[PDB]
Image (cartoon, rainbow over all chains, first blue to last red; front, side, top):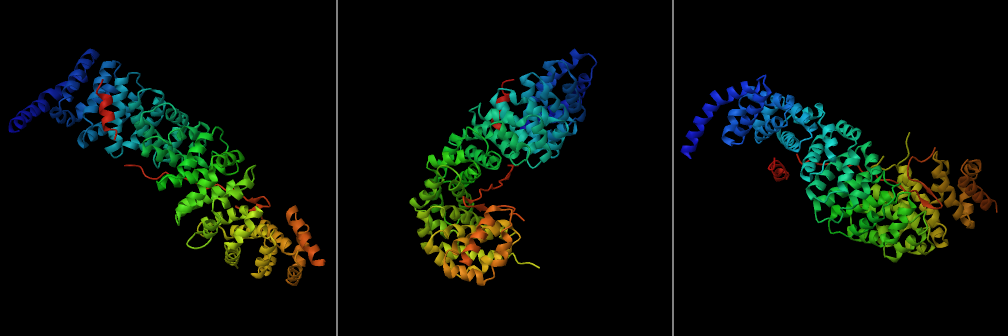
Length: 522
Length: 41
């Protein structure tokens, strides 16, 4: 080791004093053939690790290398110079030298080269810089590297694409402006194309990471969806790579709220229902979330999910989930969506009961459940109540007194001269709406009136919010068909507000009001 | 006034979107991919 140390020390001196300063002068020559030949020598020297320090520790040399690469018209020269900079980019010292020498803007310019060797040296060197040189990200952006990188996504070398996409991820993360530039360059379509074209796992992985970063952008999101992003990411949900599956899921979830109008979602929906049964908590959480958004106001999606056994799968997810609200809220929201406004809605309402889900569903209304989950669960119970067969079991699970409790608390909390992201006014409408439907049953009506709810329901007739006025009038309409209830409602002084509601632009409100009035007069 | 969100009617509760927007975590192994790419030109 002492021999090599001595020999290297001597050679380093010869380089720093003779070779390097000489080659720098030749790179600056007017004769391009001299520059070319000199560039070759510099490149050959860069291949030997021990010779690199002599090269990088000379700002004049580095600057000459960069300037030559960026200005040359000789392919071989561009190749040698880029290759040299790459050889010097393996450590902090070299990276800093390339950076200070203005290598970034030159390396970015090389991204416009038609020669693979140059592009490969350029992208890997920029990647090294992007990974370790502070200030590299801003310089690459300023030099317009994003635009050049996106334009290169049409290339076919999968290893090259993997590095190129990763540079985009590094440059785009947490930088809204970089995401818009990528969008403006047509990044979404180009990224989606890769996902449905290549099988190279490392590329799919790096590409899925860029899509995830862009999926939280309100501009890129719809672009990704329109480009077929959902279907494309769905293609890899069963791929052996867990990191890929999870990145595809996170991305799909972020995009999900803007994909409710997409067609060709059959395969995706079917796979998500299957994933609901995964042992992986992060997978189940994303599957539930994506399904909730995809079933939202899309009867076709609701129909497909039910047809692949989505009701049974979601109930099972809720049953084994316990207190994990990250899973229960979206799963319950999905069940809520599936139990209303579609051809199989009625069948889904019964299926929840037939799959032994009623007890756990009513249980979620109680502590430690938080407002988001409670609101969703009240919505689901409201839909389940549409099914006569669910009238008795729901009452037997104590749903009525719990709904009344939530209603009282939510309403009193609205008194004044957002709780856990939920407005108490939403809970008031929701619980009263659920009670209105459950009140279609005679035994339930008795339970409801026995909880002394009439004074509250009458008070709700005065609410500024007409949606609340509607459900209050409605539940009173159901209860009023009972003599004692009708008289009690009258005693509460409900005649005045109900008469006023007769003029309501809302037909439902007007009809319910009249119904209650007729019942009282009789 | 109308309800800003939620609500429903005789056909049930109104469906609602859950706004997911998790970018989270930028790991701040392509090493072999890089050397492999350059080790041919």
